[PDB]
Image (tube, coloured by chain):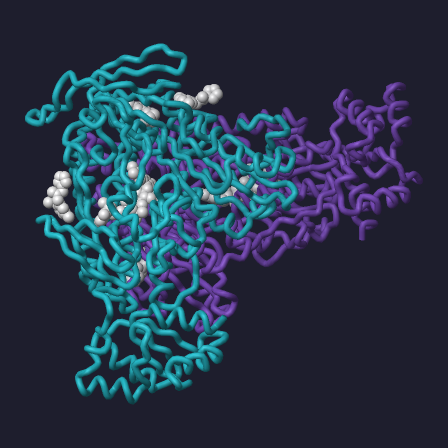
Chain colours: A purple, B cyan
Amino acid sequence: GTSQWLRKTVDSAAVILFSKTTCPYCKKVKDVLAEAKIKHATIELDQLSNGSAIQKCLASFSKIETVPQMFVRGKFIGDSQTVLKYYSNDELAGIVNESKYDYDLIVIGGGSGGLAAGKEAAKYGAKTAVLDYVEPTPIGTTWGLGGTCVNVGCIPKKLMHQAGLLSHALEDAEHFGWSLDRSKISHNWSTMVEGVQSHIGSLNWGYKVALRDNQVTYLNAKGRLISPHEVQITDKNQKVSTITGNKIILATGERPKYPEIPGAVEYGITSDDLFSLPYFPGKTLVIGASYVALECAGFLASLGGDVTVMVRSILLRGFDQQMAEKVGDYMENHGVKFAKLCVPDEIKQLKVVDTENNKPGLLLVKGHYTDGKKFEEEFETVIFAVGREPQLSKVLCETVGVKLDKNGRVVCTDDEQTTVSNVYAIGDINAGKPQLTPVAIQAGRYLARRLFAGATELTDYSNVATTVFTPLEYGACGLSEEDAIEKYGDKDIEVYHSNFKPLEWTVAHREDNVCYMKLVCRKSDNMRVLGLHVLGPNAGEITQGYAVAIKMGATKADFDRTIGIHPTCSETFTTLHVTKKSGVSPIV
Amino acid sequence: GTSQWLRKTVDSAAVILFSKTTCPYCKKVKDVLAEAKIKHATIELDQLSNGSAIQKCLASFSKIETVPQMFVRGKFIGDSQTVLKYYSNDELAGIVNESKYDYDLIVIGGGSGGLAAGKEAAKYGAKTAVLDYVEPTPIGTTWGLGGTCVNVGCIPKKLMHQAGLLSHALEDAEHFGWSLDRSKISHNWSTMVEGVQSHIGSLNWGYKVALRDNQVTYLNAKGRLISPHEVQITDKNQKVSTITGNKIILATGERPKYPEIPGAVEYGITSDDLFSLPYFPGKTLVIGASYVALECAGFLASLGGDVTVMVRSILLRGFDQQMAEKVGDYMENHGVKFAKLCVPDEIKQLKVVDTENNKPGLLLVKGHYTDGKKFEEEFETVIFAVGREPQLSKVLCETVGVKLDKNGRVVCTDDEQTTVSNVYAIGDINAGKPQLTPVAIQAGRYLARRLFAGATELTDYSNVATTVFTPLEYGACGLSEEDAIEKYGDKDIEVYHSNFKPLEWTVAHREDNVCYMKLVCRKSDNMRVLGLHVLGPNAGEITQGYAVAIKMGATKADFDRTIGIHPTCSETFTTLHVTKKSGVSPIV
Ligand SMILES: Cc1cc2nc3c(=O)[nH]c(=O)nc-3n(C[C@H](O)[C@H](O)[C@H](O)COP(=O)(O)OP(=O)(O)OC[C@H]3O[C@@H](n4cnc5c(N)ncnc54)[C@H](O)[C@@H]3O)c2cc1C
Ligand SMILES: Cc1cc2nc3c(=O)[nH]c(=O)nc-3n(C[C@H](O)[C@H](O)[C@H](O)COP(=O)(O)OP(=O)(O)OC[C@H]3O[C@@H](n4cnc5c(N)ncnc54)[C@H](O)[C@@H]3O)c2cc1C
Ligand SMILES: COc1ccc(C)cc1NC(=O)Nn1cnnc1
Ligand SMILES: COc1ccc(C)cc1NC(=O)Nn1cnnc1
Ligand SMILES: COc1ccc(C)cc1NC(=O)Nn1cnnc1
Ligand SMILES: COc1ccc(C)cc1NC(=O)Nn1cnnc1
C-alpha cells in the first residue's frame, strides 16, 4: 500500500527531498539546494495522513528512519550532514546531474498538452526537452510554437467569431440611440488577419520565453521514437541525431483530412490555411458539418461573405440533434445556404490564385445528391472540414511496441500509460478521450506531477463541458437527450425546457423564441441532471459554472432551490417547469 | 405530524381534492370540476410516501376514508356521488363560492413579489385581488403595473447599461477590421429613452393581460390594512371603501430617500425620475455610493456625460471592499470623477428646467470634506442615491398588531408569517432578507403554494448570488473576504486569486491586468468555498452557474477536478492556484 507508492515515487522522481516543516535540519538542506539552484520535489511528512508509515518505509532504501532524506533518480544521497559534505567539497552538482539518460523527460509535440506537461515537470527538477515541428500544409502554410489551438484553432477562430459578433453590435447600437448607419460600414479581411496574427505571434514568443525561464530545452525538430528510450530527431538542415530519455510523452496531435477526389489537395484549403489567408476568401463553399465547418461558415457570413455548406448527412454528429438543428436553422435565417444530403465528386480550376494583386482563384465544384441528382456551381474558395486524424506512423516505430486502436490513436491506461512502461500519451492522440485543449492541459500537468512529485490524482474525463461558437452559440454538459433515452429508457427520462429572449434583444428588435434551454433528468435517481443544453449569447460563460454542479451530482431540486441573478440569460435555468411529456409550449 | 399538516392544509385551501391517480371515480370528479371551470388544488395520495396515514386522517374531518374527497374553505363537501348530485342539481357553483370573506387572498402591492404570489394562488382556485398604486415622485413622475424592477429598476438600468457597453463595441470594431470611425459617432438620449419606455409599456400591458387570464381582480388603488381581515382602499376618484380577505400578503416595496438639506427635494431627482427623463441630464452629480449610484454614474459617463460621484465614506458598503475599490478604479480610469470623503450641504437653483426647449436647468451645489475644506461646483442635474426605505405607516395601522423592526421592516418567521397569524410579508419589506427581484418572486410563489396547495417547501435565503452592473461588472456569491476572516479567523481562511484578460480584449488593445477573480475558502472544512468574486465582462452570466455548486457545498477540490471550457473568462476559476498567503503575484 504505502510501500508500493513510496517505491514508485523514489524510482521516478529526478530529485526529491523527504522533509518536515518543523525540522530546522530540513530548512538547512532546502537552503543549500536553493543556493546551488537545484530544483527538486518535496514531501512534507507532517502534513500527510500516514506520514509515520512513510517515514518507516524510507528505511528500506536508506537504512535510516529520520528526516531529511534526499534521493536522486532512485538513489539515496544522504541525510543532513552528508548533503553539506557534498556541497562543501564541490561534489553536489555532479551527483544531482548524473543520469543514465540525456533527459529525465522528452516530450514529442509542442502544443497544448506537451507544453503544459514539460513546464510542470521542470518545476520538480526533471531535466526536460520539448520537441516541436510544424509540417507545412499542401500550399506551404506553416506557423510557430504552441500547437493547433494557439495557431490554427480555438484562439484565431474565436477572434474571428468576435469580429462577426461585432456586426450585430453595430446594428444594435442604432436602436440603443447611437448615430451610426450600419448600411454604410464594411469589413477589411486583411486588417483583421493582421491583428489576429500579431496576437498569435505574441503567444509563440511567450512560449519560448516560458520554456527558457523553466530551463527546458526546446528543439524545433521532428522527433521519432525508435526504441523505448531513444528518440531520433531531424533538424531544419535534415541533420539526424539521437537523444535518450527516461520517460517519454507523446503529444503530437492531429491534422485535417482531405476527401479522396480529384482537385481536393490541389485547389481546396483547410482550417490550417484559413486563419492566415492573405486574401478574403470571397464566395466560399464549406464541405462538412463538424463544429469546425459550422463555426467557419458562420463568421465568414457575418463578415459579408457568400457562404454555402455541403452536408453529407447530419449537422454536428455526436451532439444532441435537436440543438444541432436549431443551430443550423439560425444560421440559415441569417444568410448561410445549406446543400443537404450532398457530397463532392471533383474540384476543377478555372483561375489560379492571384498572388500579386491579393485575390482568390476560381473553382468549379461538381457533386451529387443522395437520391441521384447533380450539384454543379462555381466558388472562389473551397474549405474542407471533414475531420482530423493523427499520423503516428511518422512519430512511432512499430517495433517499439506501442499499441494503437483501429482509428490510429494510442491505447492507454487511466494514468495515460501505453503498452510500453515508460511511454505515455496525452491530448488528441489518446484514444477515446474528449479532444479539447483544457483536457490536454489537465492531463499533461497531472501526469507530470505523478511522475516527478509523487502525486496520485488522476484526470477525470467524464461530463466535460463544451461550447460550439456558431453565430448563436451552443453550450452543453453531459448527455444528449437521445443518449439518455437510449441508456435508461424513455419512461425514466424527464426533460424540462424553455425558450427565452435576452434583455439585450428587446430594444434591438431581435427574435422572440429562438434562444432555448433544457435539462435532461433521470426520474428514478432523484431527478439527477444527466445533461444541460443552452442555445444563446455567451453560451460558454453560461455553461461553465454548471459543470461544477454536474460534477457534484446536481439534481433538479438543486437547480430549483438556487436563486437566480436578474437580469441574465443564465437565470432561466433556476425556474424551469414545463416538461416535454406535458405537451405545454416552451415559448414565452 | 401528518395530522397537523392535514389540518393546516384543509383549513386554508380554497378548493382541494384528495385523489389517487389510478381511480376513475376521482377522474370523474376532476372532469366535472374542469367542465364547470372550477380551479382547485389536487393531492395524489398514491404519490406520497405516507399517503396511507393521510387517508386515515381525512376521516377526522369527513367520517370516511376513501377517495375522492373534496373540500371548500375548510369544509368537507362530498365524495363522488355527492359532488355529481350537486352538479346536476345546479348547486355546485354556489357551494364553491361560499365564503366568509370577499377574497381568499388580498395582495397589497403589485410588484415582483406581489404579482408572483397572486398569479400562483389563483391557479389553485383562490379568489384573489391584487392592489397596486404608484405614489408620484416630487416632480410628478409615475408609471404602470409591475413594481420597481420593471419600471424604475433592474430592467431600464440594464438596458441603459447595454447602451453604454455598445460604446466600447463601436471602438473595438475598428481593431477587428470594420470601417467605422468611433470619434464621429454620437448618442441621442431621447431616442434611447423612447425604446426603453416602449419595452416597459409592453411589460405593463403583459401583466394586466396575465391577471385577466388568471381571473385575478386588479384594483389600481391604494390599500391600507385596518384590521387582520379588512383592507381599506382609495381609488383614483378618492372613493373610499373596504374589502375583506382570509389571507393577506403585504408586498409594498420601498422608495428612494432624500437627504435633509435645502433644495434637495425641490431641485434634485432620483432613479425613480431618471429612467423616463425627457432631456439628457447633462453635467451630472451623483450623491451616494450604493450599487444604484455607481451603475447610474457608469452608464451616464459611457453615453458621453460629464459625471461626478460624491462619496461620504466607502463604495458598496456591505460588499467585499477589495472588489469595491477595483470597481471604482476602473470607473475613474474611464472618466468618472470622484469627490471622496464629501457630503452635500445645500442645492441652489440657478436656472429652472426648460420644459419647452427640452433642456435641464442649472444648480449650485455646496458641500464639505471630512477635514473641513469646502466643496462648491455647478451641475445641470443632481441625482440622489442615498438609500431606500419602506413607509409602512401609510400601509398598516398600528392597532392591527404587525411587529416592525428598527428600520421599519416587517419581522417574519421563516415561512413569511407576521405576528398576526393570517398576515404575511414578502420582498423588500421582509426584515433581514436580501432585497432582490428573484428572491421576492421565489418567496411569493412558494408562499402561495403553501397557503393553497398544501406545499411544505420554504424559501432558502442563504448564499444568494448578486451582480453589480457597473461598466466593468462585479459578480459575487457568498461571503466577502473580510467577513470570512471575522467569522473563522485569518489562519483558517485561504484565498486563491488571479488576474485575467478576455480574449476579446487582445486585438482591441484593452487592459492586461484589470479583470480579477478570487475564491475565499475554509481550511478546516476541506477547503470549502465560502465566497466567489469576479470582476469582468458578463459577470452575471459567469457567476450564476457556480451558485448551484456553492448551494451544494462545493470545495476547492470540486473546482480543480472540473475541466474548463476554452476560450472563456469563466474557465479561469477551474485552474486557480496562487494563494494570497504565498505573496506570489496574481498577474498573468
Ligand atoms: C479549427 C479548430 C478549432 C478548435 N477550437 C477549439 C475550442 O474552441 N476549444 C477547445 O477546447 N478545443 C478546440 N480545438 C481542439 C484543440 O485545438 C485540440 O484539442 C488541442 O490543440 C489538442 O492538443 P494536443 O497537445 O493534443 O495537440 P496539438 O495542440 O495539435 O499539438 C501537437 C503539436 O505537435 C507537433 N508535432 C506533430 N508531430 C510531431 C513530431 N513528429 N515531432 C515534433 N512535433 C510534432 C504538431 O505540429 C503540433 O505543434 C479546435 C481545433 C481546431 C482544429
Ligand atoms: C435602481 C434599481 C435597480 C435595481 N436593480 C436590480 C437588479 O439588477 N437585480 C435585482 O435583483 N434587483 C434589483 N433592484 C431591486 C428590485 O427592484 C427590488 O428588490 C424588487 O423590485 C422588490 O420587489 P417588491 O415586490 O418587494 O416591491 P416592488 O417591486 O417595489 O413593488 C411594490 C409595489 O407596491 C406598490 N405600493 C406601495 N404602497 C402601496 C399601497 N399602499 N397600496 C398599493 N400598492 C402599493 C408600489 O408602488 C410598487 O408598485 C433594483 C432596484 C433599484 C431601485
Ligand atoms: C441537416 O439539418 C439541417 C441542415 C441545415 C439547416 C438550416 C437546418 C437543419 N436542421 C433541420 O432540419 N431543421 N428543421 C426543420 N424542421 N425540423 C428541423
Ligand atoms: C389620479 O391618480 C391616482 C390613481 C390611483 C389612486 C389610487 C389615487 C390617485 N390619486 C392621485 O392623484 N395621486 N397623486 C398624489 N400626488 N399627485 C397625484
Ligand atoms: C472610496 O474608494 C474609492 C473611491 C473612488 C475611486 C475611484 C476609487 C476608490 N478606491 C480606492 O481607494 N482604490 N485604491 C487605490 N489604492 N488602493 C485602493
Ligand atoms: C470604455 O471606457 C470609456 C470610453 C469612452 C467614454 C466616453 C467613456 C468610457 N468609460 C466607461 O467604460 N464607462 N464608464 C462609466 N464610468 N466609468 C467608466
User: Residue B110 location in percent, x, y?
Assistant: 24, 51
Query: Which residue: 46% across, 63% down?
Result: A521
Q: Residue furthest left?
A: B356
Establish if A495 lies above or below A75.
below
Q: Is residue A226 left or right of residue A444?
A: right
Q: Residue at x 34, y 68 (%)?
A: B12
Front-most of residues B290 and A298: B290
View quadrant of ligand 5 = top left
Residue B279 in percent (x, y) is at 15, 28
Residue A312 against residue A207 in the figure, above or below: below
Residue B317 quadrant = top left
Residue B415 is situated, as x and y percent measured from the top left of the image, at 41, 57
Q: Please name the residue shown 23% across and 25% down the image.
A: B264
B21 vs B463, left or right, is left
Query: Could you tell me if residue A141 is visible in this image?
Result: yes
Q: Is residue B452 left or right of residue A106?
A: left
Place residue A207 in its image quadrant. top right
Q: Position of residue A22 (x, y in %)?
A: 79, 32
The residue sitting at the top extreme is: B373
Q: Nearer the viewer, residue B469 or B373?
A: B373
- Let me know if residue A312 appears in the view: no
Camera-side residue of A97 and A395: A97
Q: Viewer-proximal residue, B578 or A332? A: B578
The residue sitting at 22% across, 31% down in the picture is A185
